Image (cartoon, rainbow over all chains, first blue to last red):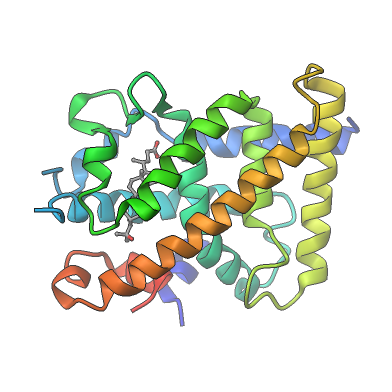
Length: 10
Length: 237
Ligand SMILES: C[C@H](CCC(=O)O)[C@H]1CC[C@H]2[C@@H]3CC[C@@H]4C[C@H](CC(C)(C)O)CC[C@]4(C)[C@H]3CC[C@]12C
């Protein structure tokens, strides 16, 4: 449930 | 030091150089520094920015990108505050016990960091931890390996493939131990690996004390109001 972390990862 | 070990170290050095700026230029783009909560907005901005840089460093750790996105998320969530405290050692000066990102405007001492709704129960050990790390006089090669070993840790909560995380970590650990033997001058190398892992233990403890105070701080909406969306996603709502 971590959309901003997910975005900074990709 | 195999060819593989030399590659790991060179990749981690350049990753760090790409992701850490001790001139702290972008700190102009934060809410400006200024009650015992006057520094919370600025220092929430600094931590939020620094999390992005930790993720940058993390993605360049060899084998990291071979993890699932689930594992990557949980490793970063639990390690972020630790890696931020750890990498700050390069800007820390024992001259006056401050983090001195060049300018007085972006010079943080015990008075500054004490004004963001964290108590000295967190601040005093954080300053003593910096003094301890300065006293080990680490090579930057050892610095960046410790940051990677901090992040890729199979004992972190929520890890799915602990065996794969452990595998990455052993390769990093072996590289660090081999570096200390082949490259760190004795008797400075004596139990240096062990003193480094203790420093990781001091980061876990600082981490859990940061958690407790954040859990408190954040339960007060006037304070949560001054945080960032990224800080709320990473540390919790
Ligand atoms: C200035 C320095 C970095 C310099 C560099 O990168 O070179 C950094 C590194 C560690 C930082 C502390 C970590 C623990 C605290 C987290 C809360 C974050 C919050 C969301 C409010 O919980 C803000 C206040 C505290 C005390 C931070 C103050 C700034 C410090 C000392």
